[PDB]
View (cartoon, rainbow over the protein chains, first blue to last red):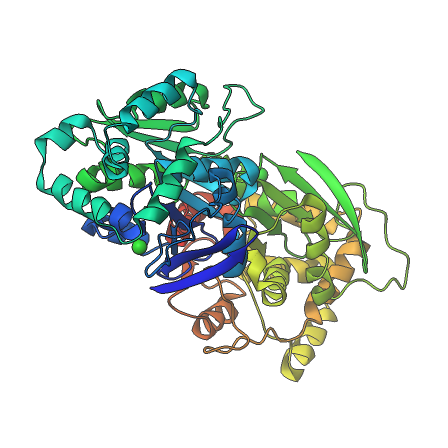
Length: 281
Length: 281
Ligand SMILES: [Cl-]
Ligand SMILES: [Cl-]
């Protein structure tokens, strides 16, 4: 694995490349959720045994949001962190640096929004998208009021945790939940994480309409946990996208982070997703 | 199907496009043998029922050598016909005109030489090659002496026929042989065909060496008939190419033009060839 950084209009971004480029295939490019990094977000999936057998035949580029990279400095107080749209705009710089011309994007939560935005802006560079927990809607006033009321008695880590996991997972307090609670609550870059969180909260409508012009032009696999926080947004997202090109993997017993709890079934879905795109997997 | 022509440094070339471009796949591009056109060379294969089910998922560009296109004028006496290398050099113009960035080339005889030459010159545009009856060696003096001796008592059509079919096929005189004999002997563009024939005869070494630098960098399927005229050249070609990337389909009972006599088995080989490249077929 080789870690790189590239300069962009909005600051430096770090990414780690794994594997070897397969002739005339897209790179797999990932973007992680708020509170996480590529490792805490994607390691259980990309290191799953069945996944390793698929990804041998791809090069992989795992992006860390600015400030999330290993050994990131804490951005200065009052720093103007990139919006999600600006984050999406760092990806052309990444690909140009690597000389990769096309990708299959895999994103979770804010990372899914970013990869969707990227795909709208650069549709000829995107062969497919796996969009986990995607919520393409800006908060409306009712959302802002509820969020701010919640914020009065919840810490920043508790709120990020509530974005990642269901209330029931957070109450049940499994070993995975305990580990992720410590990760976020005691992160040395929590100030950086909070800026990314604010980004996410302030994102604009990703404005899919079934029947163009604002539509995704590529195969999409939508993923969400049954009864998880983002379920309604992913369901709604499924009704806006082109049905001939879109599959919806709504998983029972996966909770808020399906790529962490059910990497085996997700892997198998990815295999069929690649096959339906026309790649042997 | 849409027929197009493009201007090049060496004159106009015609080509017919079939099907619809499949996102992020190579176009299938064909180049026919001496004495034929894309139709007399490739129709039994590309219209084979099993083939139609594969090629639904590709756009196809069938090139007619200059002078072989429907309604071609007879080139003026003393015309300087393109060498095979110049013919190979017309292909960048074809692809640029269509805005296609990569191909899988399928060639027979002189068309296989041309597509191989093209691939050496533009390796990043070639995803794979099916090379039928390829003979990458210039004639040496012993070859020239034999050819010219043969020429004293054989007509131009008889010699072209002997390039396409085995002596045993030509003696046995099947219905296919009768049809192809009439096609060539009574072609209205025979003067054009003869110029292409002279091209072929005057070609230079395509200088494969097992271990680079002059080597094909892509999957290759070599095809020849058992005991057919080009058998030894294809066998020799197989020993120069990279074994990890090269498959050799030496067909029993196919004769001089395997794409005409065994399109079903050739189709099935093409399917596995695509699968080994990493495309579902
Ligand atoms: Cl990986
Ligand atoms: Cl066709």
